[PDB]
Image (cartoon, rainbow, N blue to C red):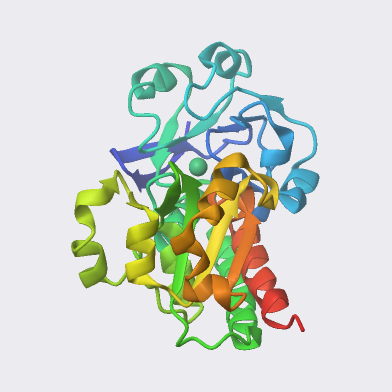
Amino acid sequence: ASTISVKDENGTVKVPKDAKRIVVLEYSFADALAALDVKPVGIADDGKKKRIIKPVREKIGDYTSVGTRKQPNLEEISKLKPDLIIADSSRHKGINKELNKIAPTLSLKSFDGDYKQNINSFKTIAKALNKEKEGEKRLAEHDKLINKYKDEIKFDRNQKVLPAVVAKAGLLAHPNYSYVGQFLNELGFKNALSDDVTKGLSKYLKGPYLQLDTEHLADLNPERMIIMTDHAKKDSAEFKKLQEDATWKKLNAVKNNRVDIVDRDVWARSRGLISSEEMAKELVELSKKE
Ligand SMILES: [Cl-]
């Protein structure tokens, strides 16, 4: 058993050179494998096939679900007898000992990674699979496409942007150091949540995100909002109440048609090469509307 030594979030892992059958426990890792022409044998897909973004899903084809990302089914992982498991370094600390009894296990950032950290996880996966050159090629293509979309996005970058999900009668905002915040910065946007602004709102943190009620949204008054919702729907009971709010109606972004509702699976959950390309393409399209 010859191996390739790579670094992951727990130290060194010796990955077998004959690793071909791989179980992945986050969506971004499925994207990584598809980009490298590898079809995972198992995916933690939350029992929801549509959570795997379409071009990735269609390239991989048939696979076995191993359950939720929160609580993967280790009997189903065992039964697959994989060569390698790719686990999330935040979600899967508790199951790590059990996963290592089944197969060599890489522990990589996805859930608590920003945009650059997710691309770093892609690089580690490529190296682990003896596909370093293929990964370099793919990332050069990705970067060229992202910068082409950047130049086609017509929006005025002086209009500061707030990315968020809907929660608890307000918005649960993704700050400038989140995956989405950092990606928007890569596209030349200015996040409304500057470091100074976020410092002055920190009593409202809920883990990685900032809970903004309408009073605090009114004070921030970002010129643009991107609101990520399941299925890109805007008619949830929660989001409808938020809008009957007198303060919401006076917001600059609302008065001027600069609130866009986008798909949460693509924008928040996927964290892949294909999904980030799709986010950028969507911004081009929105910017070219009448
Ligand atoms: Cl997620």
Number of on-image labels: 0
Residue 103: x percent and y percent?
48, 23
Q: Is residue 269 visible?
A: no
Of 9 and 268, nearer the camera is 268
Of 242 and 211, nearer the camera is 242
Of 67 and 241, nearer the camera is 241
Q: Residue at x 47, y 83 (%)?
A: 159
Residue 269: x percent and y percent?
55, 47
Above or below: residue 85 compared with residue 261:
above
Hey, which quadrant is residue 273 in on the image? bottom right
Left or right of residue 257: residue 84: left
Image quarter where the C terminus lies is bottom right
Residue 217: x percent and y percent?
38, 63
Of 200 and 264, nearer the camera is 200
Hey, which quadrant is residue 79 in on the image? top right
Residue 229: x percent and y percent?
60, 49
Above or below: residue 31 compared with residue 201:
above
Q: Is residue 206 visible?
A: yes
